Length: 414
Ligand SMILES: Nc1nc2c(ncn2[C@@H]2O[C@H](COP(=O)(O)OP(=O)(O)CP(=O)(O)O)[C@@H](O)[C@H]2O)c(=O)[nH]1
Image (cartoon, rainbow, N blue to C red; front, top):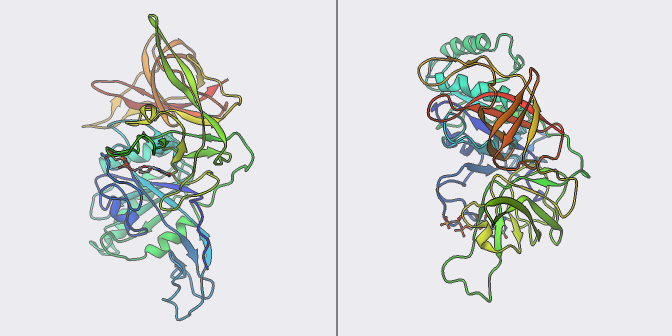
């Protein structure tokens, strides 16, 4: 007997156009976004790739083949049941991680990361090296480099890459980074991969009783044409619990909440409505919590949720220490080189009265720095961020040419 629990952790998977994308998660999980997702999504447009999978490790068997994903501990000559472990969730970027459409949404979700790089591809790959950059900028705790396409080339050439990876990871934040040989469209050493996922990207440490905070990443009016008024419920909220515990029947609010349309000015009056329900993937749960992705039932006017309206917001408890600021101050230390198309450019330090792009967890606001110092500056954002911890991390971007590109990171000071 294996218990049905909500995901408990969250791992993102990125890399160049190097294969397999969704295929690797699929090689670990099953059916999900973004073409179907059942029984979850009844249609959609673009967005990210989400899939959670059970993970159990079999005691009777031998490492690493002892690692399983379902209760069928067959391939070890024993009828014994595994020891139920974790409920890992996987999220990936179908083409929005970096360089295009920066939201940081899923980026704040990373309890770890998998940098996949095809072995048939010369390392380091252009786009992949900038992927490794964001992993240090957004500071994803615990990552692993998975050599894909290992089946394409000899182990010996599979080591010509190993060199280059170790060579690329000389004196960086990741020296003990794992490099896992794995196969794409085929299932080779995937279980060993699991092992590492169970060692390097370990089950996180959290505090059961802290400030419940969820981060709206999408919202939609679930009622489709033909739902009669007598029978319908307020649109749900996407997002993910980052701290604390949420329950049904529990009163919460979203910040900054609803914008105010009056006079010649504009503000934001936070929206107060309760949690109708919880539901992780297929099943409908009872007490939302960190790890994995969730969707919350509500009493809002669906007009408010429809079309990912609230996304980039933040769900917090009915009443709490929830500073919403039209001006922020962040310590920092930016980079010196910006990579991308063609070759890396020379990026100057933050300029005064300049408009930068600030991504705070689930949000991405453009603000103007109203005073610069060495380790710190103040930014006049156009949309009120909803700070909550002196430790929160913001990603700064500057529009060099057409759009914005990551240039540094810093903590919000309050
Ligand atoms: N977790 C959870 N999600 C719910 C619940 N009720 C409705 N939903 C959400 O409603 C969605 C149903 O999809 P759909 O009604 O077609 O809206 P949509 O995904 O925006 C599709 P379209 O873009 O065509 O309008 C699911 O993805 C699910 O997240 C619930 O009680 N719990």
